[PDB]
Length: 113
Length: 109
Length: 103
Length: 111
Ligand SMILES: [Zn+2]
Ligand SMILES: [Zn+2]
Ligand SMILES: [Zn+2]
Ligand SMILES: [Zn+2]
Image 1: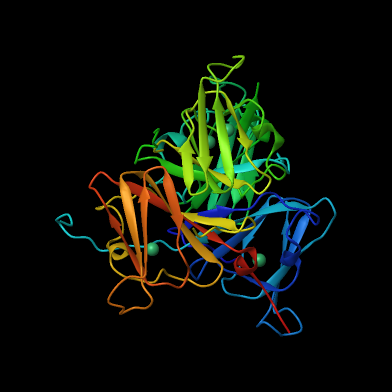
Image 2: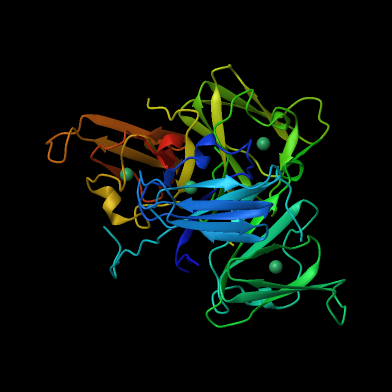
């Protein structure tokens, strides 16, 4: 399973969504982006099941990776990778958390005058 | 398993923690600060495994609820209940997300 | 002006709301609570105008505090104080950010 | 004033920064990381005042946009534009919130 580095930071979260409430576009092929690159999405299924479908590129015809996520489980998605999800039942609902890399700026001994 | 209602709101997320970076007191029997009906914490473990032990009350000798959370899994804990977690390995790391009911986030007159 | 202490941390944000998309209960008298006491709400108006009506207590007949927040401005709401907001137009829309004391 | 469209989504919020705690790079002319159409930063001042300076390009001699932000106010800055900020006082602190269009956060495939 793909893991999010322990030093990554949580930036945003989505409300709980189901087939009807989620933005329609999440069920079609797409890329999850942020302000910066390398954002890791973490989809958690609270009930039912959710399927992740990843592709080689923006136009490949069939998925090159499939992950089934059941209630009580989560899966982090490969960054900058085209994909779409699919709800397995009408009762399925889930939410998504996004994580980004931390910034480490070198500092000096004095303050900036 | 405990499930958090669809209308609940994500209010806070703790950073990733391991045996060393997490608040020492989380491994000791405690009551989540501010816990009350409508406040559900969700613990997801990214690596290793975390064990949750729940107790009927502050001084119960044995727990009445045991949950082993592995990497790729999460568990929602019951509010207003004494408990504690335990990291099963040194490289274990998890984070906790909190969700709360709209009526308690904004209590009307 | 009421200010949020520099050491507080941002915990949550609401999407942009207007008279219709906002949760109804916000236009009615209420209290913002959050998991811990002392939370600070910061309402910023992106367009139109919002008015804050604060009250002495849960049942005061009239408000003891009034603040008009116009586009390009925000206002920090006194914690633990009952209040309700009023959008001044249909075109008005705002969002709320919440800040809490350092963990 | 620039306004962030009502359907945009809050993606990041920086902690409160002052003349010393803010990343040094924000005080010098730069181009925000990942800046592009659909990404608007919103800088609001909690105390003191902050001044934004925008430039036509990277080497323009003079700025062509100036926004003074007092405490209790905020200003949305244009995307893909060279700029820098200046804290008017030592006791000044502020924070920035970034908002992004839904079509940019979730880039739909085309054919
Ligand atoms: Zn996605
Ligand atoms: Zn706990
Ligand atoms: Zn309120
Ligand atoms: Zn900037």
